[PDB]
Image (cartoon, coloured by chain):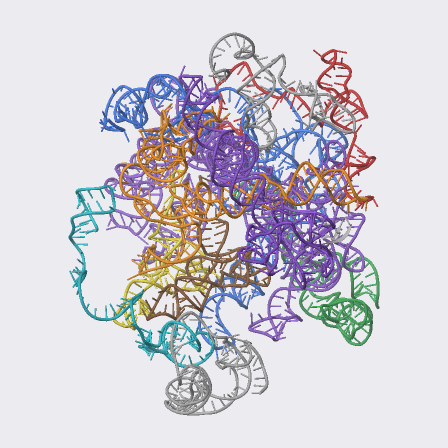
Chain colours: B cyan, D yellow, E brown, G red, H blue, I orange, J purple, K green
RNA sequence: GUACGGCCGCAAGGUUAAAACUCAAAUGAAUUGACGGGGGCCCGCACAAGCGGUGGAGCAUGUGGUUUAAUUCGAUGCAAC
RNA sequence: CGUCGUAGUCCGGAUUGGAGUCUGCAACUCGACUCCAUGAAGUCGGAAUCGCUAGUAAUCGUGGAUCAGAAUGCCACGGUG
RNA sequence: GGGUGAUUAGCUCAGCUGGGAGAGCACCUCCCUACAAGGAGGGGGUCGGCGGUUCGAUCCCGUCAUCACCCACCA
RNA sequence: CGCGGGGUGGAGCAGCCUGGUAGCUCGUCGGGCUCAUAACCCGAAGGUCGUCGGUUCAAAUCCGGCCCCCGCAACCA
RNA sequence: CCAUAGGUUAAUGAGGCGAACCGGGGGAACUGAAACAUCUAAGUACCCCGAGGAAAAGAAAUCAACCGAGAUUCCCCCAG
RNA sequence: UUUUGUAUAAUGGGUCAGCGACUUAUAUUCUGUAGCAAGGUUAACCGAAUAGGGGAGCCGAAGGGAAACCGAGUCUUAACU
RNA sequence: AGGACCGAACCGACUAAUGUUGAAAAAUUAGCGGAUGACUUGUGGCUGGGGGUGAAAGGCCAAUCAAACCGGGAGAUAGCUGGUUCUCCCCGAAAGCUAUUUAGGUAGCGCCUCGUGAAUUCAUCUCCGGGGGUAGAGCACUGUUUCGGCAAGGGGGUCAUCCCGACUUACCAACCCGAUGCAAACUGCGAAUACCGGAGAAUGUUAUCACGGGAGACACACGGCGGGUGCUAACGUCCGUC
RNA sequence: GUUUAUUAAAAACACAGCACUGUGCAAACACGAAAGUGGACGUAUACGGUGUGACGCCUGCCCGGUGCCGGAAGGUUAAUUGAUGGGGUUAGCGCAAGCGAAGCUCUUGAUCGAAGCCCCGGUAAACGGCGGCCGUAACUAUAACGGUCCUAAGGUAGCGA
RNA sequence: UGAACUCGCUGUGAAGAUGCAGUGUACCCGCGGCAAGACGGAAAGACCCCGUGAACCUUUACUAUAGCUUGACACUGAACAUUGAGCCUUGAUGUGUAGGAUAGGUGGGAGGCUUUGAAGUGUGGACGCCAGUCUGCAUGGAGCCGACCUUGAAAUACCACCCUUUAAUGUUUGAUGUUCUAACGUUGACCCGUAAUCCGGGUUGCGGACAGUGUCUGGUGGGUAGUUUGACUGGGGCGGUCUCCUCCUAAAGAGUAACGGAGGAGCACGAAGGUUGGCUAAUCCUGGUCGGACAUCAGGAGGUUAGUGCAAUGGCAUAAGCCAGCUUGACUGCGAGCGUGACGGCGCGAGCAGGUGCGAAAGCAGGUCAUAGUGAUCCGGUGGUUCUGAAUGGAAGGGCCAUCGCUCAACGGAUAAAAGGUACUCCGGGGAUAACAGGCUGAUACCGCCCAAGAGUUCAUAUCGACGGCGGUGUUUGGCACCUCGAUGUCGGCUCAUCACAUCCUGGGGCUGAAGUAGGUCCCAAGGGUAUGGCUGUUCGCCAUUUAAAGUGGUACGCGAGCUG
RNA sequence: GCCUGGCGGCCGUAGCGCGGUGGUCCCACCUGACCCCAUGCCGAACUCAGAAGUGAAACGCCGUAGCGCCGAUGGUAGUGUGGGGUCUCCCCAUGCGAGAGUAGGGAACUGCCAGGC
């Protein structure tokens, strides 16, 4: 048994992602996270695994 | 036909064949019942099948088990309660 | 003729809550009746096995015997069939 | 000598937070029906002996003895 | 010394390992076929699935001790 | 039959020997990898064949890099 | 001689004699010493084989960065910090 | 006739004895035994190294053999073994840390040492300040505990159910009054000594530091002291420590 | 009869006979890096492989595992076949992005097939295997007995401190 | 064969003296004869233990191979038939609905086409809108078709392109069998070389597209061969431990040993993070409906004796505990410096820019209450890359930047690939390490004394003793690991010594539950004494008969340079 | 001197028991609640506006040497270094020295600012 790491995609319109461990057996519903990005040098939301 | 020896067989076997112990018996025939998953003709409501029930609830009225001081003694398959 | 409408309740009535009817020496405990509320079980019954046939089954009325007092029991009468 | 168990009815024995007398067969009697069957009540218990504790030692636990069965010495 | 398991109606053995959940045969207590018993058939009565805490929607089941056991191995110099 | 295998006669070539070197053939294990198989060690060791005064190589369907080389072998280097 | 440690009942020695052991081979560097010095040095070979030539090649004086690329600077870097 | 009874020649190993630096590379003396056979033997051949030969012991294979003998790779390899040199001097270790197919070696730290450059290296005494909980002391809190008394509730037993329900607490355990033992794992207290640095006196060592070169050791043993362990035993055991 | 030279001599080994297995003969089988020979100038009353041990009386069950045979229909399935598509290059095309003809070079995987193995049946005189627990008579004790966990199945005949 | 004026004790000593301490004994050397002693001699011990030594014994360890088995393709052929499989080739197709009319799709379109072909229209076969077409007939046999009429996006001669389903001809390729020689073969026969069993040449039969063999290859194969094959432990095996975290033993710094004393980890929370605002327990008692025995919360009594992701340690209400909002700082790239381990690795942190969030602002925010939650190096796969790929330009490839993973967990990891056994071995080292013996100790062992619950019909102590205590002994069973593994013969059997005294017998006698004879018990004493028969490897044991006894112990539990084995 | 409030310092001499004591001043109760503000509901809390009531609770001071707390001198426990022995203890030399109690101390002291007499 493992919680597994999933990739949330940046609102920068690219394939760039942030990985987090998110167990489908405790919280399967979608998540969106605000983080800093050093390429746009400002904060963006990372959302959804597909 | 159990035991012992002798004879005979490749062998399974073939032959001779007791004693002790124990019981008023073993056994042939004919006779009449009764019994059968036996026979033939047959009847019963017995089987069957068209229905009603008792078996489940609560209450009553008898019989066992349980129990005390007595909780009475028998009847108790068809033939009781 | 109106009215309710398969419901563990609407139908069903047990152990209740209260006051009354009665015989007798006397019904607290073992008896019956009545009136006004309350209320449990009860949705045709386990295996199995029991009884029948026209005025018979089922169904609804009445009397009487036993008896100080009390039986849906016992013995007779009749309607619907 | 020592080791580990047993000691409760003739023979076999049950009973592990310490409140234990009970069963089978053995021995009699009654009802059964004349007996066996079936049913019931009785006769017989050092629950081994002796210390410490205690409300009290089948159990906390020391020791004596008999039965059980087993050792030491060459490895 | 332990290791892995077991903890079940009276006896012997299932289920478990998937919480929505105590079972079968021999027995014990009666019904049915019987004259009568057994088989067979239909019914009943029964287990705190060790013990105290914990975790939980919940604990015979998981988690920690304690406690009683089964089996395997209890000899190497 | 002719023929030819076979038979005979004459001639040439080889044969055996000689120190070391040398082309080709057969071909390890140890050793190192502080351990072992690939890799290293080694085409060594030893054995075999064969041959010359030397054996072996060569002047390109080779080697470079747009510059060009213009046979091979031997030496110092390229280069740890 | 072995050992922390042996007069040691711990191994060893009959005795005299001839014998018997840390090197040179190569690369690089540290030290010494010296020549030259931002330079130093030659190898094979040539040659008058202990002269003189031969500087091919090597060691050195510039660094930063995987590297492209930059250079008294440079990589990190939007950068100055 | 004979895988027949005894038995010369012929063969031959079983018992016994002698021998055992011998006569001896296996014999000698006496006996029992093999002797038409699955036998024995004269003479010459044939079977070879993981191959032979074996009615089969890994016995025999020229004395050798869980793999013969000689010559080569080979002076293979040995964290081991021991052999490792004539004469005066300067400084002066270790058997500890950390890692390793690690507990026989080796590698970073501790300990030894030579050169080079720049230089005093240190402690004891007194007092002041600072981080400090061992020794001792203790019962407050934890856990444990004795003695005396009261004792909720739980676990056990009993009799009443009318007397205000009552007796009992050997067991498990809360409250409480009065006392006492234990503690590495506790604290209503805590030294001696040690260690760090000032303020101050006294004494004498060429020192300390960096760089550039070499090491040696990381299996020692013992008496005392500080503590566990062992039977408050061992020339026993495991450490600290002088 | 055989058994090792000088401490290990018999019960071990061989033998008369017993069984199973391979062999139709240019046998099967073996040695020979082979040329060849042995098998054997033997031919099923004859040879190769392995165990048994004269003679007399004699031979229970198990094919799950590991071997072997009968069946090859089915499954599993390889090298190989290599339908489809992609990567590299390139004449060429478009403003660029981005596209791209042919030939080459790499690559992919639609999918087939032998033997084995599995599957079905047999094979133990093939290598082998032949188990436990619980309860139970009319004293003690035992169980002819009944169950129960399991295995491929868990001992007919004979011997036994 | 070290040198030797090499006598005995009790001590000491790497603990057995000859050589050291004390003490005791002795004239010296030949001749013959014997051996207790000189840790004996020949052999670096075989055996026991340790171990990044060797060799066998084995096995689906790793790997290979002889032997065997499997298929295409080749030396190596003519062809024939019958057909499994794939593939090419071709025809029928094709409608509804309303109307002549089955327009398949679709691109062209008036002179062009069918003779192996159309009609009939059905008997009968498939399909079916029952019409029609095909298989093949009854059967004929060069045509035909368009206008007018009218459907529809679209036309009905003539001619391309595209197809479902399906069979036969063809074709590639496996089977089944067919004849027949020529690759191949004869362990057939004959003639000749040749008074030759081989070989060569010829002859004449019979086999054979078989065999034999090769390239490549699926599979097998301990028969043969090379190699790998964990550790700690005041002994081994089972068990435990092996990397990470904490406390105590542990010493008024740290380190610091013991299967000394005891517990945890190899992750989880997008929330339980951030920040601003508000608040804070336990426990008992009292008291009250819908509530079956108990669901309510208010008050007092009182406590930092509640809560926190978990070990133990310590923190925490200024809360890190419980909530309310806003929120995502669970921030990026970096960094003076400090602490720390030998390094790997890591914690703390001033300072800079950029972008967020809470708040009035100060101030805080580059994660959770802290201490455990992994796998390097090597590398396969993949996306990017205005780094590079050495003839030039691309590019397999190498680098850089993203993305992931080996319980390799023997954890700090010996290699795309490695397991067991040796009493059949065997090598280097050793009492560093056990066994038979020497030392140390005396719990164990046997005994006495202090003392006394009791037994001894009274009575504790004649004789005997549960309990507690303190010794006598060297001495056993064990503990222990010093001197011993270049080699101390072990058990029993025979044959034969020396010293003790803890006395079995022999001499002495005491106490007594001793009148006497005895029994029970005590101690002065080691001068003399202390069997034999049967069974067994034999002590140990048992049995029968003898005896003043049928004593105990030390001497490696005495006598292998003694006998037996 | 005295009284109080804030920041506090020091933190038991600052404690406990029991008693006394203040409303000019400050301090708390108190007296009300639109608005800004607040409530999973509420002027309860938070918050505002103030003087009719009071010196109670709350806040602050103080007497009291009974106990806590601090604790001399003497002795004790322990101990650094040294000598011995009768040996995990004792004896000696030479230094250090708690813990508890006693006598004594002690019912504090104070920096900055501000109000009051």
Q: Which percent across, then down, holds residue H140? A: 61, 59
Q: Which percent across, then down, holds residue J496? A: 32, 31
Q: Which percent across, then down, holds residue A19? A: 69, 51
Total of numbered circles in the picture? 0
Decide if residue A32 is in sight here.
yes
Q: Nearer the viewer, residue H225 or J369?
A: J369
Query: Quadrant of residue B6 in the image?
Result: top left
Q: Nearer the viewer, residue G45 or H195?
A: G45
Residue that appears at 65% across and 57% down: A28
Q: Is residue B69 above or below residue J341?
A: below
- Left or right: where H161 falls relative to J446: right
Q: Is residue J212 above or below residue H25?
A: below
Query: Quadrant of residue K71 in the image?
Result: bottom right
Residue that appears at 64% across and 57% down: A26
Q: Nearer the viewer, residue I36 or H90?
A: I36
Decide if residue A27 is in sight here.
no
Q: Nearer the viewer, residue G72 or A11?
A: A11
- Left or right: where I87 falls relative to D75: right
Q: Is residue H175 above or below residue J519?
A: below
Residue that appears at 63% across and 53% down: A3
Query: Quadrant of residue K95 in the image?
Result: top right
């Amino acid at each position: 048994g493992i919680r597994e790491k999933i990739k949330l995609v940046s609102s920068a319109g690219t394939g760039h992602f942030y990985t987090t461990t998110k167990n489908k057996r405790t919280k399967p519903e979608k998540l969106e996270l605000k983080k800093f990005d050093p390429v746009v040098r400002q904060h963006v939301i990372y959302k959804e695994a597909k």
